[PDB]
Amino acid sequence: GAERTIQLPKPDMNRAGLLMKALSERHSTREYASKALSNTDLSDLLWAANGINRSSEGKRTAPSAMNRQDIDIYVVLPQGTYLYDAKGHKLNLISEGDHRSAVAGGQAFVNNAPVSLVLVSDLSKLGDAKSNHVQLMGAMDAGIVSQNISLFCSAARLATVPRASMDLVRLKAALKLKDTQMPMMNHPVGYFK
Amino acid sequence: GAERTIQLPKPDMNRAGLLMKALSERHSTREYASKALSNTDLSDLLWAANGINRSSEGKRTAPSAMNRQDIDIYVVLPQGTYLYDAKGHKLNLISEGDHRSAVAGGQAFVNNAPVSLVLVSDLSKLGDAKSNHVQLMGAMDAGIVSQNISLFCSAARLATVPRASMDLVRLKAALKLKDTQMPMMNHPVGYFK
Ligand SMILES: Cc1cc2nc3c(=O)[nH]c(=O)nc-3n(C[C@H](O)[C@H](O)[C@H](O)COP(=O)(O)O)c2cc1C
Ligand SMILES: Cc1cc2nc3c(=O)[nH]c(=O)nc-3n(C[C@H](O)[C@H](O)[C@H](O)COP(=O)(O)O)c2cc1C
Image 1 (cartoon, rainbow over the protein chains, first blue to last red):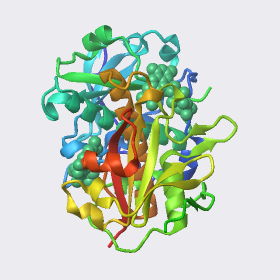
Image 2 (tube, chains in turn red, green):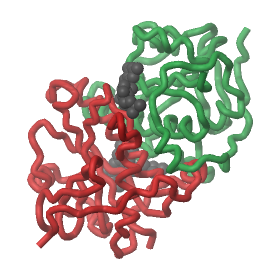
Image 3 (spheres, chains in turn blue, cyan):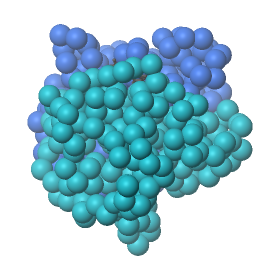
Image 4 (cartoon, rainbow over the protein chains, first blue to last red):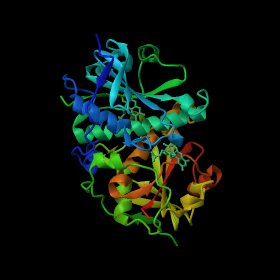
């Protein structure tokens, strides 16, 4: 069955790709090559999204409210759903099997991407999970991470689209989410077709 | 008095600066050189934040929910507060005088930055402004724009910090905001001291 930990290679924090060109070419794509992302590309993508960029401080590529670091990245692959661990550049298995449909919700195109990243805010890290103000903070934090992903994909020539739509009942189950974890956004990612 | 329109130079969409290095060096800074940003730097910053990257389609560097393009960027300078117009790469005067304190709220350090960008979601472009779900969309959209700014600043060697705090009463007045416009975030920006 699925590996309980996928060890990804060290991210290449010096990878080619101009920011300004990444901004110019930043766009949503809803069609994907079928092939899996290389582990190099998946590693670099995850570090860009919300990796540790200052080791001694444990701080991240993505800012967060009060440095609470509330956004977790779940990685939904055909063989299983994993949770990104930035401290080890590794993925820890959450649930076996293919849960892309849960990410897709009503949009079938999403199942065509070889991987989806799901941005889930752990609202308890921010305050009262039932507070609208706390939710708005988590939402802001998710958008921050989303644009790291979109820009990385543009620089790296990967297809992606930021999405808010998903089947929350099936996704809660698939990602084994607590009631205080709120899925905010997701990103199907693949090579261009 | 203040120019009613500041015409900024065409943004240099091919400006030096690796994305991966921008990610590595991305961090919050709460101290600033006193000198004003060059108009070149302010132009490039605003285009990165939420410029038009596909002219024929009118689409932007920052994605938005349904392409509703809800995030407006107000630019708070010593001489006046302006609204960024992406279609003309220009700034249109909203209110004369220095309104940095309104952005600062309880944090006096903010008045030390020569410019602050205020990210205001026009919630009516998204739906019912009173809906929590609509607000969460606007918040996500603001975070997207925020991280464009943070990454640009890292690439360009500008100091910035994403903030949610501000004096909303004084800011509403200063930016002449409608009830359906919700300030979400702000970014003091300057050169490093
Ligand atoms: C949504 C959001 C709201 C924030 N609000 C404030 C704020 O009001 N004032 C401030 O000084 N910093 C604010 N911060 C900056 C965080 O404190 C900062 O991101 C955090 O300490 C991590 O530091 P880093 O950005 O260097 O990684 C905010 C950050 C985010 C993402
Ligand atoms: C917060 C947010 C939510 C979105 N939700 C969806 C979605 O559920 N499904 C989808 O196909 N696109 C979604 N989009 C993508 C937008 O439709 C897209 O950004 C917009 O059409 C502009 O296109 P562009 O990204 O190429 O600039 C979302 C975008 C954002 C920022």
